[PDB]
Image (cartoon, grey):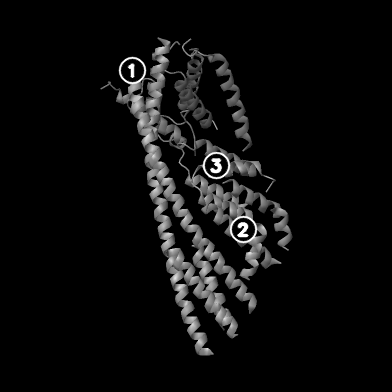
Amino acid sequence: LPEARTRFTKSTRNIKPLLSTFSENEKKCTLDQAFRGILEEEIINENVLAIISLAIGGVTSTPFVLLGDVLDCLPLDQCDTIFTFVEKNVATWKNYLLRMCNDLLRRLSKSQNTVFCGRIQLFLARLFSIPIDYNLYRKFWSLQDYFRNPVQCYEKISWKTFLKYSEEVLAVFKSYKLDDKMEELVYFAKFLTSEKLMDLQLSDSNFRRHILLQYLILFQYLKGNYVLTDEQSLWIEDTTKSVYQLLSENPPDGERFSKMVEHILNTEENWNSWK
Amino acid sequence: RDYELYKYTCQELQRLMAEIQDLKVAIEIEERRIQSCVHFMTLKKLNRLAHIRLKKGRDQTHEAKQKVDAYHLQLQNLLYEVMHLQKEITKC
Amino acid sequence: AGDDRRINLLVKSFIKWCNGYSQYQRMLSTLSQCEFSMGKTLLVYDMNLREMENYEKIYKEIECSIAGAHEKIAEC
């Protein structure tokens, strides 16, 4: 019985001789244990792992388990090369793929591997000192916390704070008046909640576009218990007509961008009507 | 050394099951069963030690990953400040 | 915790054979699978130590980039 598994490992050490000397459930079990031992020896020693996985795909739940083992044994970059190999060799291929992707998403960092997180989610979708205004800081990021939880905009006190803070922030946006050929002369993914900056962001137009789009997405969500005061609806309509005017006042092509936002939000209403 | 002791106890258990397969007397069967049960208890203790060491290493990686993420966040703040000042001077 | 269930299945098969060559093959197969799992765990530990070394290598690089960024701020 160990003579058999040593015979199979001598058959491997290339594909034709292995397929010849491999010549029934226990035989396939000894084959799988032989591939486990060979992949372990090659992990102790990258490309040869891909060669063995191609040989296993040529023979054939064993390659799922073996890819899981090799992805659990290699640190960062070699897993990226193996993930490129998985994206190349699809062949329409279940649960072990989900386990590998979940363990990868648990193992990553989301600071230097956000692109790789996006690739994993695409694969899973394919299968299935300076003076600082602290008051504007606190009110602005409290509005951000209100954007992150849209359920909170149905009570009384939270809605009143939302009214006060949003009207103050839109007043600041109306009163700053950027009026910018400067753009004619590394990607920041999340917001930078820093006390010290707070003014280089207000001088930008992209930051204003993100905040006004986030207002419009919240207002389109609130139009779709859970009752609204008519005064709140009039306030929503007034602020919506103001936010469209503010997006028209962005210096690069505000009218075309506002038309795009209008058509996209109408199609979002049509999409939300389905689900 | 832990893996070597693991494989040595596996060799012991292989010798005992070969002894039972060649024997297939109650006293020898009971002695082989007791030595094999001692082997199984050592294997379970070694498995417990391996899983404890693996969980310790995983948490020890995770804390350093969190600290690298925070320090990279501060670096992203400073790079945004540099980029805005450079765009402002190219404007001016 | 699957190694404990494999050890329980191996102990159950040993108690069943103790009270038959296919069960001997099954015992050898489970023994080899447990050996492969024990060989896997140390490689996972070494991979964790290599990731720790990589994070501690990246940390000083981010320190040096911050040290350059402050000088760029002052010059600008």
Quadrant in which the N terminus of chain A is drawn: bottom right
Q: Secondary structure at mark 3?
A: helix
Q: Is residue A268 above or below residue A256?
A: below
Mark 3 residue crowding within 10 angstroms, few (<14) / some (14–19) / many (20+): some
A177 relative to A32 in the view: left or right: left
Dot 3 and dot 2 within a common chain = yes
* Residue under label 1: C75
Q: Secondary structure at mark 1?
A: helix
Q: Amino acid at mark 1?
A: Glu
Frontmost of labels 3 and 2 is 2
**Distance of label 3 from label 2 (alpha carbons):** 22 Å
Dot 2 and dot 1 within a common chain = no
Q: Amino acid at mark 3?
A: Asp
Identity of the residue drawn at 40% across and 19% down: B84
Front one among B19 and A174: B19
**Distance of label 2 from label 1 (alpha carbons):** 59 Å
Identity of the residue drawn at 43% across and 66% down: B46
Proximity of marks 1 and 3: CB atoms separated by less than 8 Å? no
Residue B5 visible in the snapshot: yes
Residue C13 in picture, x, y percent from top left: 57, 75
**Chain letter of disc 2?**
A
* Residue under label 2: A35
Proximity of marks 3 and 2: CB atoms separated by less than 8 Å? no
Residue B75 in picture, x, y percent from top left: 38, 30
Residue A52 in picture, x, y percent from top left: 63, 51
**Chain letter of disc 3?**
A
Residue A182 in picture, x, y percent from top left: 46, 12
* Residue under label 3: A80
Q: Amino acid at mark 2?
A: Phe
